[PDB]
Length: 241
Ligand SMILES: C=CC1=C(C)/C(=C/c2[nH]c(Cc3[nH]c(/C=C4\NC(=O)C(C)=C4C=C)c(C)c3CCC(=O)O)c(CCC(=O)O)c2C)NC1=O
Ligand code: NA
Image (cartoon, rainbow, N blue to C red; front, side, top):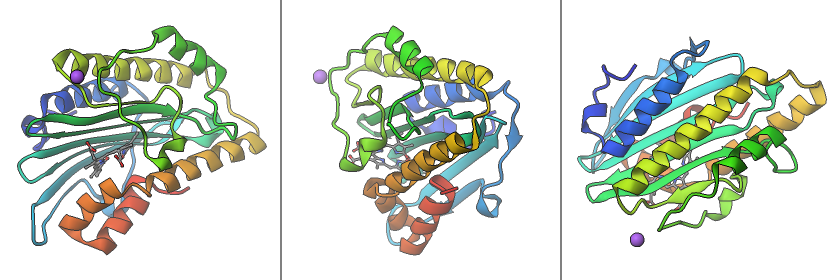
C-alpha cells in the first residue's frame, strides 16, 4: 500500500493516479515479497548536483517473476514512475511496462506497453484480440520510439499528454491493459521446455535493449556515479535471467 510512501504526496498528480491504479491491480493477487539486491527499498544520493530519491516496491507471483514499482524524484522538479511486470517464462505472458516522466510544467513522457517475448515479436493471440477491441486511442502529441525500442509492440503508447483529458485517457488505457493482463494470467498454461526457452530469450533481449536507454542512465549517473548506475540498471531495473 502507498499511504506510507514519503514520495507519493509530492509527485505529479498523474503519477499519483497511475501508482494507485497499479497498486490496486496487484493488491489481491497471490503476492510474495521479492528481495531486490541488498534488500533495497529507499535510497537517496547526491554528488555535485541535485539529489535523487527512489522508493522501490517489488513482489512476485507464480506467473510474474518480478513486479517492480519504483517512484523517484530528482531535486524539486523531476518526478518519475517506473513499473515493469516481468513474466515467468513458463507461462509465456508478455511484459507489462510503463514509465511517466514529469517536470514542473507537466508530464513530458508517458509510455506503456505489453511487449512481446515470442521470437516472431507478436503478442499471443488472446492479447491481440482483446487489445484490438479497445480501439485506437486518440492523442494529439505522439512521440517516436528510439532505435532500441524495437522491443515494443504495435500497441505501445508513447505520448506527451496535452491536457488533463489526455492524462486521464492514458491512465485508463493502462488500467485496461492491466485488466487484460491479469485475466490472461489466470488462463495461462505451463509451456513446454522449448517454448519456455523462447520466452526466456525474449525477456533477456528486452532487458538488454532497455539498458541502452541513456536517458535513464544519465539521471542515475549524475546522482550516484557511473559504477553505481551500471549496477542499478543491470541488477535492479533490468536484470537478465
Ligand atoms: C530510475 C528509473 C527511470 C529513470 C531515471 C527514467 C528517466 C527517463 N526516461 C525517459 C524517457 C524514456 N523512457 C522510455 C521507456 C521506458 N523506460 C522504462 O524504464 C520503461 C519500463 C519504459 C517503457 C515501458 C522511453 C522509450 C523513453 C524515451 C527515450 C528517448 O527519448 O531517448 C526520460 C526522458 C523524458 C522525455 O524525453 O520527456 C527520462 C529522464 N525512466 C525510468 O524509468
Ligand atoms: Na497539442
